[PDB]
Image: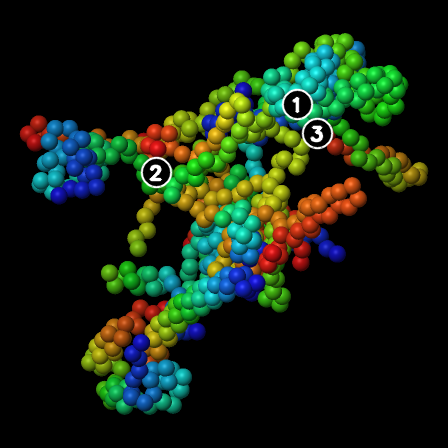
Amino acid sequence: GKGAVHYTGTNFRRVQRLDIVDRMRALVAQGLVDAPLWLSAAERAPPMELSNLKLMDRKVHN
Amino acid sequence: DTATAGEAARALERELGLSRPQYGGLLQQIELPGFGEINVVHGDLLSG
Amino acid sequence: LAEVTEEERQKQLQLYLQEKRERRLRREEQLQRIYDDKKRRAVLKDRMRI
Amino acid sequence: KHLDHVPTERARQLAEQRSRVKLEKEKFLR
Amino acid sequence: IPDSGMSFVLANLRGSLGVFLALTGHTLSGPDLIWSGLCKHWISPEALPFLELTAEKQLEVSEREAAVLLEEHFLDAPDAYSLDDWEEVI
Amino acid sequence: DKVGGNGTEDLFDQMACARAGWPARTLLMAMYMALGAKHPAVQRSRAELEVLLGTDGFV
Amino acid sequence: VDFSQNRFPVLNTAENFRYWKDRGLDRLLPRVFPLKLPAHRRVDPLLREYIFFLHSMDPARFSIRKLGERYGLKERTVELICREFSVAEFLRRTELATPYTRRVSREKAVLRMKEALFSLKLGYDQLGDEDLDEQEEHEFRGFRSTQDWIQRQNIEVEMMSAFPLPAKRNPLPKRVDVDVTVHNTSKLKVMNWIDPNDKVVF
Amino acid sequence: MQRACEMVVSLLRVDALSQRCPFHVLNVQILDLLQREGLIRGFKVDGTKIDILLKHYKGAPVIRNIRVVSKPSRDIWLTPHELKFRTRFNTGLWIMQTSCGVISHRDCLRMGIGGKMLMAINNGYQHFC
Amino acid sequence: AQTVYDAEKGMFVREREGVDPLIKLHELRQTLLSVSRMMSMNKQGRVYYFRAIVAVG
């Protein structure tokens, strides 16, 4: 057999990026952490999706 | 084809009388001799 | 059996008519499309050969 | 196969010419 | 004649500005639209791809929160107004 | 559905066979060869032919 | 108070589906739940005797349906009450066995203990609390109730549109064979084997 | 068929805004089905190539898996009551080709028609051949 | 210093650095998947240590 020969397969990991608001909401809902004081402000001002904007960079011929 | 019953079954029902100009009329009647009668009728109370 | 056969004959006739008509329509559509395609291709080829 | 018809960007450009300026991003200094 | 609500839009302007526009065929461009009131906001087209890419928090915030989040893309238009000294005459 | 040319071999036959003949086509081909590709008249006629036949803009 | 992206404050939500049911490490807590008891064993024995008397006297005026209607019970419950009381009275009056010498199964002995402790704690009900004709209520009733067996799917994936969509193919009732008795005597039982697919019926 | 099995690779890209694949009418129809199912942001037809603009959500891509069923060296066909069993209890998209066009397994199941199983999108781990 | 009293245990337990203090350790549980006796070699001979794999959720 082989290892990392599965291109378009298990070579890459398709996992979601969970930011602070998502992780803290999950922790609070599951009750593993007491609601922090900053959480309300973070939720009312959610972080932007940086990966989508990153995908917009395009190589240009010089 | 297996969904329906069939013309044979329909004709058998018609011959047996089970399923053989707007209101049916007297559909049922209970007669208590010496006491009276209870009728069940398909009819219109007001327009009829 | 005669009653059931009359019913079945009606059903089969209707099914046959439906299938025939729809297959005919599909063939007509396909033929029209292919004919138009070939019609444009022939003129294109003639211009190229000119 | 060279007589087939498939939509193409060259065809679109030719149609427009029969009928593309690049623009620089603004800076929003203020 | 104007149609598709164009008459409503023209009549909803201050004074007889809409009537003047529809009758004289006057062309207003740029912040003139904002100052006349035809268009509420002044947003650059660069936001539209940005909105497409960043609309995933609309489902992380509530409806009103999302509606206010939409306003981050409104800019400040130049103060120039072609018909500033003509509304009274019109 | 009316399609064809020449009179005996239709366009569907001209497409299929490379040896098929067509005097109307050969008239123009001979005129082009006898004037030259660079000739302004030849260039105008060829452009007109392409446009009228409706095969211009093909990719 | 957690967050929801959409407004739908009802009891018919995945969060509220099986309300109060453990969804974390508390699933391993040894909780004690109320024990279930039959209604025909919850109602008071004197009420049982009264129902049995009425039914054994005039089963027409005091129908099973009417008795259940008056005493807040089900027809099956009334039938069970009457059967049990008739059996007990037959045994007592014929002097065959006392209420504590009739051989029974372990399950029924445990049921008797359950009702004894139920009466000692709360006391027998003086009236029925059932419903005559149960209603169409959205409740979890086992794993079989959580899926569409015919479709073989737990989730209905569908598109978003403001216009009508093609209708779903309806199932057709299964056509299974049945036996219907047609002539029964003290010696012979004759029943017609019916095949609902046979087209020619005569 | 070869072109579709090739386009699988272009669809399974990660950390990419858009990717190119070979052109074919079958590819165009499968892309139409995918866009109607909301799995891609869009696509563009450019001569010999098709440029698929992919869709993402919370970093990860919407298309998490593609399982090929019908290969050019082996067709796979199913009756309606076999398709129902094979797609049982799954939210994935199984692309089916029928006499009525390239549709989803749910359309095929409602129509009760025999179809050819091409691809399975986001079907998790559910396959038989 | 830097210890917390556990009611059920009735005793104090230390607070460990690296752990996030916000996390409530009383609502997490662990399972030992595997423990093995690995070996190393030095000048005097063979040295034994241990490896462990543990799941926490």
Q: How far apart are the alpha carbons under marks 3 and 1?
A: 64 Å
Q: Are marks 1 and 2 on the same chain?
A: no
Chain letter for the residue marked with disc 3 in the picture: I
Amino acid carrying mark 2 in the image: Lys
Judged from the image, the secondary structure of the residue bearing numbered disc 2 is: loop
Chain letter for the residue marked with disc 1 in the picture: G
Instruction: Point out residue H102 in the picture as x, y percentages from the top left corner.
Output: 49, 58
Residue C16, relative to residue A21: is it above or below?
below
Residue E46, relative to residue G200: is it above or below?
above
Q: Residue at x 60, y 56 (%)?
A: G201
Chain letter for the residue marked with disc 2 in the picture: D
Amino acid carrying mark 3 in the image: Gly
The residue where tag 2 is placed is D27
Q: Residue furthest right?
A: I44
Q: Is residue H39 visible?
A: no
Q: Residue furthest left?
A: E89
Q: Pick whichever, G86 or H43, lies toward us.
A: G86
The residue where tag 3 is placed is I57
Q: Quadrant of residue G112?
A: top right
